[PDB]
Image (cartoon, coloured by chain):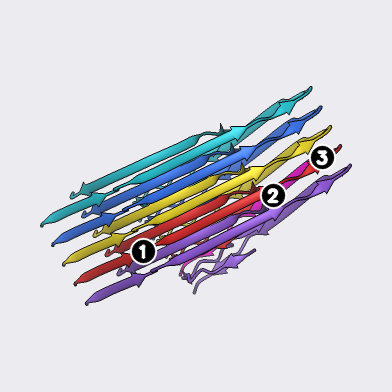
Chain colours: A cyan, B blue, C yellow, D red, E purple
Amino acid sequence: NFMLTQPHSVSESPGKTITISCTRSSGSIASNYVQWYQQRPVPDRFSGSIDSSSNSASLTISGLQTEDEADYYCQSYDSSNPHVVFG
Amino acid sequence: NFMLTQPHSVSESPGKTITISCTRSSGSIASNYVQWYQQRPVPDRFSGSIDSSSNSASLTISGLQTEDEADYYCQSYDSSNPHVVFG
Amino acid sequence: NFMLTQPHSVSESPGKTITISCTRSSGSIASNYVQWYQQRPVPDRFSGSIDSSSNSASLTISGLQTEDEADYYCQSYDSSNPHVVFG
Amino acid sequence: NFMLTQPHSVSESPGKTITISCTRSSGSIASNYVQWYQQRPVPDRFSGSIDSSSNSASLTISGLQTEDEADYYCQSYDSSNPHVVFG
Amino acid sequence: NFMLTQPHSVSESPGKTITISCTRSSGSIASNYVQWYQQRPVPDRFSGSIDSSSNSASLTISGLQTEDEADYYCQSYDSSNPHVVFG
């Protein structure tokens, strides 16, 4: 899958950031995740409860294959040359 | 799947950010996720309860294949050259 | 599927942002997700309850195939060259 | 499916943003999703209750195929070159 | 399906935004979704209740096929070159 779940703030920054190319992924994730992120460049209270959690991630591939003749030709080209003038 | 769920704020930033090309993904995710993100470049109270959660993610592929003669030719070209003038 | 669910704010930023090409995805997601995102470049109260949640995501592919002669030719070209003048 | 559900605000930004091409997706999603997004470039109260939720997402493909001779030729071309003058 | 449900505001931005081409999607979605999005470039109260929700999404394809001789030739061309002058 593609869980692109990122609450990110971007200032004036002409670039490319995340770039994924020619990647193969296959796995299982079971996560109980708690985060308090505080950035201050008055009272703060954080309460997080997960309680009883049952996370199951099962992947089964019972395959059989004869002659494959596999040719995995993955070519990736990425060019990023921004031209930014501030005035 | 494609869970593109990101509450992001972008300032003046001519670019490309996320770019996914020639990628194969197949997996299972079971997530109990809690986040409090605070950025302050008065009273803050965060209460998060998950209680009893049962997350099940099952993937089964019981396949059989004879001669495949697979040829996976994945060619990707990406060009990003912005020209931004501020005045 | 394609769950494109992102409450994003974009300032003056001529670009391309998300770009997905030549991607194959097949999986299962079970998510109990809680987020409080606060950005302040007076009283804030956040209460989130999930209580009893039963998330089930089942994918089954019981297939059988003979000679496939598969040829996966995925060619992608993306060009983005904006010309923005501010005055 | 195509769940294009994004409450996004776009400033003066001549571009292309989301672009999906030559993509194959097949999966199951079970989501209990709660978000409070606050951006302030007086009293704020957020109460969210999911209570008892039963989400089931079942996908079954019990197929059988003989000789396929599959040829997946996916060619995608995207060009975006805006010319914007402000005066 | 095509659930194009996005309450978006677009400023002066000559572009293309969402563009979907040569895509195949087949899946199941079960979503209990709550969002409060606040953007302020006095009292705010948000109350959201889902209570008891039973979401079921079942997809079944019990198919059988002989020799297919499948040839999936998907060619997509997209060109967007706006010329906007402000005066």
User: CB under 8 Å between callouts 1 and 3?
Assistant: no
Amino acid of disc 2: Tyr
Q: Residue at x 59, y 56 (%)?
A: E28
Q: Residue furthest left?
A: A42
Q: Quadrant of the N terminus of chain E?
A: bottom right
Provide residue B63's location: percent of width, then percent of height.
Answer: 71, 35
Give the magenta-colored segment's residue range: D67-87
Instruction: Determine the residue positioned at 79% across, 22% down.
Output: A67
- The part of the image, by quadrant, that contains residue A43 is bottom left
| Location of mark 3 (residue) | D70
Whether B54 is among the magenta residues is no
Mark 3 residue type: Ala
Q: Are marks 2 and 1 on the same chain?
A: yes
For the point 33% across and 62% down, the residue is: D37
C55 relative to B1 in the view: left or right: left
Q: Main secondary structure of the magenta part?
A: strand
How far from the left and from the top, in percent, is residue C36? 29, 57
The CA distance from mark 3 to mark 2 is 23 Å
Q: Nearer the viewer, mark 1 or mark 3?
A: 1
